[PDB]
Structure formats: structure tokens, C-alpha cells
Amino acid sequence: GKNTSGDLSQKQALQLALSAREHFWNTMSGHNPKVKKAVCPSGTFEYQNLQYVYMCSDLGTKAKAVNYLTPIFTKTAIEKGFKDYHFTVSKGKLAVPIGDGDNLLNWKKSTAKLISKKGSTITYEFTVPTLDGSPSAKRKVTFVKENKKWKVNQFDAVI
């Protein structure tokens, strides 16, 4: 190839995807390790028959956590990924249910393919090789420019 058009391209989509996987897994981990000076309350409680953990002070409220995700994810993608994972507030502090997750998907070795390019919305497909040595998985990721920055339209789009 020797031609480019639109505004978002294969490199940008791939890095946006890696950054979204980094932000999602660190949010599910109860704390963003990008901050070393966060106050971690370390307490737990019970809600909807699950054990919940409180977030550290840079994710300490819904506003704090939305503000951390805003650069990567659209407002509606963040609100959807709060509800779908049962994110809540207790005693003024953000909390998330106890669990664990990890994918064999090697996104650092994945490659992007354009699917659709329509004004303020663009879609790429990703061929993602595995750390197991199994054949590469296919995934699809849509990016939307919300004002002046391209953001992922889904919180769990890349993991």
C-alpha cells in the first residue's frame, strides 16, 4: 500500500487498543499503578451477594474513575462498563466486586485491518496471536471522536 485517508490509521488504532486493555485491566485491579501517591483505604463489604473492594484515591469516586478513562473511552462506553461490571459507591467511595481475569491474547504482536471509515466513527479488525501457540483470534474495535480525541466506544473492547 502507498495511500492514507480519514484521520485514524492502523498504528493509532493498535496503540489505542493496547492503551484501552491497559486501562481496563488496571481498573479491574482496583487501582491505576500510573499513580504511586494514591491513598488506598484497603477495606471491603458485601453487596448483591458479592464481596466489594474500595478503589484508591485517584479512582476514589465515580468522577475520579470516569476522569481516568475519559482519554480512552467515550462517556457512554464508561457508563456501560460501570453498569455491566456492577461498579458502585458505598460511604462516598467507589467500589468494584472481587474477581480475577487474564487473556492468552498477545496484543503487542497483533495487527490492525480497516473495516469501516464514516465521519466521526471508524472500525478496525485485529488479528491477535496467542501465548498458547494456537491460531490467531479475530476481534473488532470501533473508535469515535467525541470532541477532539478518538476514543473506544466499548470498555471491554480489548483485553
Image (cartoon, grey):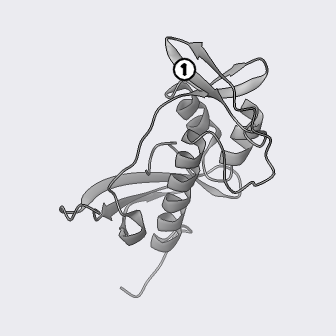
Percent from the top left, x then y, of residue 106? 36, 63
Residue 80 pos. (x, y %): 54, 31
Residue at 70% x, 39% y: name it: 65
Whether residue 77 sits left or right of residue 156 in the image: it is right
Q: Quadrant of the N terminus?
A: bottom left
- Residue lying at 49% horizontally and 73% vertically, measured from the top left: 11
Q: In this view, does 137 lie to the left or right of 42?
A: left
Label 1 secondary element: strand
Vertical relation: 116 (above or below) 83:
below
Mark 1: which amino acid? Gln
The residue lying toward the viewer, choosing from 80 and 85, is: 85
Picture quadrant of residue 126: bottom left
Among the 4 quarters of the image, the one containing residue 28: top right
- Placement of 71 over or under 95, stated as above or below: below
Residue 49: x and y in percent read: 49, 11
Q: Which of 140 and 38 is in front in this view?
A: 38
